[PDB]
Length: 257
Image 1 (tube, rainbow, N blue to C red):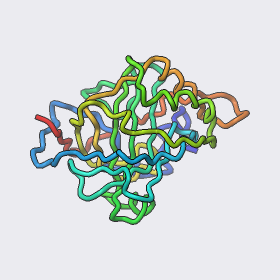
Image 2: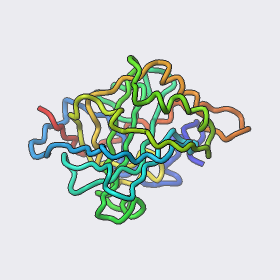
Image 3: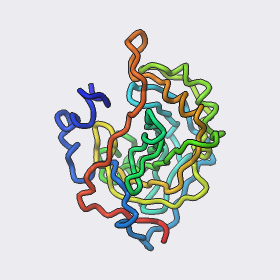
Image 4: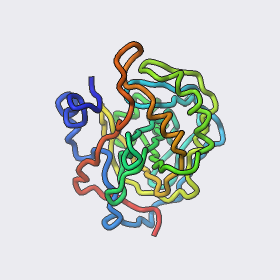
């Protein structure tokens, strides 16, 4: 099974998933020098007033959250998006050192971690059908930097022990995505893919420029999660990030001047 180790990491994914070498792979390094302001980008719209989180889980790859996507309670519109995209999940890629952890990089700089909020184009009926489409998903990436504690993350941090091993999950109805959003919504957008197998190129990436802060203690708790299952030898869930992939001449657009 795929992973992040020497024998099953990103260097191996292409064998089982040949698209790993596609023309629209994620993540990419955001080169501010080549990125270009796109005046035709409409204002980003994040409607997260209605709560929809159902539970937190450990799938042996990364910490994640599943949200109730039965209705248009938490959606993403505007920016480069055509239509309405419904929030279905969130995943956290984390490093083993504060100097690394993010999938996307800005001018080669890596952050301690990167949080993703996955949305699907409601024109496709459901998540499953959406991921088979070039414009089926819209993913909001948020960089995490070490510093002040992030209030909207403490509730999760206190119950991480309950989902320490893969296959574990806990009910969690108050994971408010509004509480992990930065002050500014400035972002870079580019056509890409999922950052883990199946690596489908069905994603419109919206990476927020401004990172949020989280305390050392909060990061340390997420670094205590396990890639392994219960009773199995311990493998800390750290460095579960894919390195920057070939841009292949794709165009990264900025929402700001």
